[PDB]
Length: 225
Length: 225
Ligand SMILES: Nc1ncnc2c1ncn2[C@@H]1O[C@H](COP(=O)(O)OP(=O)(O)O)[C@@H](O)[C@H]1O
Ligand SMILES: Nc1ncnc2c1ncn2[C@@H]1O[C@H](COP(=O)(O)OP(=O)(O)O)[C@@H](O)[C@H]1O
Ligand SMILES: Cc1cn([C@H]2C[C@H](O)[C@@H](COP(=O)(O)O)O2)c(=O)[nH]c1=O
Ligand SMILES: Cc1cn([C@H]2C[C@H](O)[C@@H](COP(=O)(O)O)O2)c(=O)[nH]c1=O
Ligand SMILES: [Mg+2]
Ligand SMILES: [Mg+2]
Ligand SMILES: [Mg+2]
Ligand SMILES: [Mg+2]
Image (cartoon, rainbow over all chains, first blue to last red; front, side):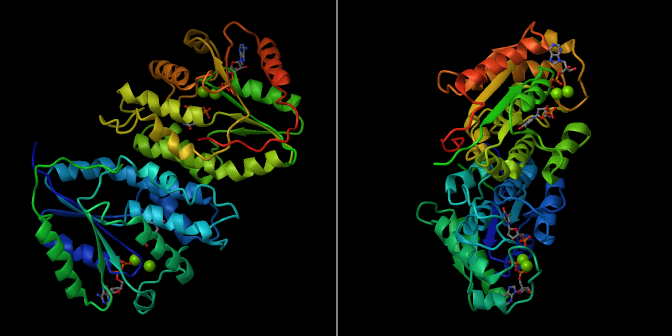
């Protein structure tokens, strides 16, 4: 069919290096757009931002999970169009963040993070995934993994709802549980413990340059199933 | 286990008689609560209300569909609790409205009603249903069916986004396609053409009184799957 750019997703915990490497990679990729999730500029995004930033605000975990997926569906069409025009697209967070942050509440009791004692559907990975099905699949997913101790040493803690170490630990496990690189070879878990900014960039670039994710291709856009 | 009230859902098109019969039935049922979907009082509800009432407002069909389901998940816990305390609950619209109004956009081209030429997932009944899975199943679902010509004669057209006869026709078909009373005997399609307010009430009541949906039961709450 025709030429297109590629979709490259960076996942990870807070302060794992995602926005830093996303910008650096927008620079190496050309032409390139950078999209952040959640997109707090959209109308659903502003709700999500209330939820994350005003910790008195009330919303069931299932409602919240659905808002995050709806927010991606606000951008889906635009993403496809840009890719098909030959743009390279860097995502900072996406469907893996969606599943993992919600999945982690399932055995976690903290009235701020997870409202109420019932955890209905919060361990059902298929329910959690189903609203993101049909969204564009990244051509490459890069998961940046790191020690909680190393994260605690960096600037960037912002007092949002999920920014609690005991919860972040559960989220770390949930991410490694849903990221299976044998069942899906588009996924690359990259250990960034004790690596500088440039060393990370060099590793990230090598993975990209080797699979040729920086070059146009004649494949169609894959979709999440 | 313990006693509970019952969940009785009234579905139908606009002006098919739903709010009228819901109030009348809150009166016959005791103790009773009436819940309307969408619930436009919640924070997601206010978004839904923007979407329905400000026809210049922009939102992808998939995002919109997800908001409607999220809105039900705002109320899910409360619904269960009230039922388990012995309250009878009347719903005016629910998951059937969710699927049908979105499913109907799939072969309908009108930039107000359905933004953009792609209809991704809008014919996939499983995607459409999946976010409502795990919500409480009504014990009885009553679908009020009626001619479009009879509807056009009644007061109640409010200029909201979907209030176009050519779309309403597609929605009517979608409802009859997803409501299968053989595969699910909790569902009752009731023809209300040429029936007065009281004649409808008498028919609705007979169905309820006969299945004993007005009485407490020792069954657990069923859930959508
Ligand atoms: N390899 C690294 N070593 C040390 N600090 C880093 C590294 N990468 C990023 N940082 C710094 O740590 C902080 C968090 O990085 P950031 O890229 O904002 O993470 P995220 O975008 O995942 O929340 C920033 O202050 C950033 O400069
Ligand atoms: N059986 C009926 N015959 C004639 N008019 C009716 C009947 N039931 C309701 N109405 C009237 O038609 C209008 C629409 O009814 P309503 O119950 O508001 O429908 P919905 O709640 O489904 O939008 C109201 O003005 C109402 O009084
Ligand atoms: C994209 C996304 C983020 N999140 C969480 C991760 C962060 O705590 C929060 C905001 O992310 P940010 O700090 O990277 O903007 O949202 C979800 O719970 N679900 C999602 O789908
Ligand atoms: C409950 C619900 C309503 N709808 C539509 C039907 C109506 O056009 C509109 C508002 O309903 P109302 O007029 O009964 O308040 O919302 C959906 O599209 N999805 C849903 O899930
Ligand atoms: Mg961050
Ligand atoms: Mg932070
Ligand atoms: Mg009405
Ligand atoms: Mg109306």
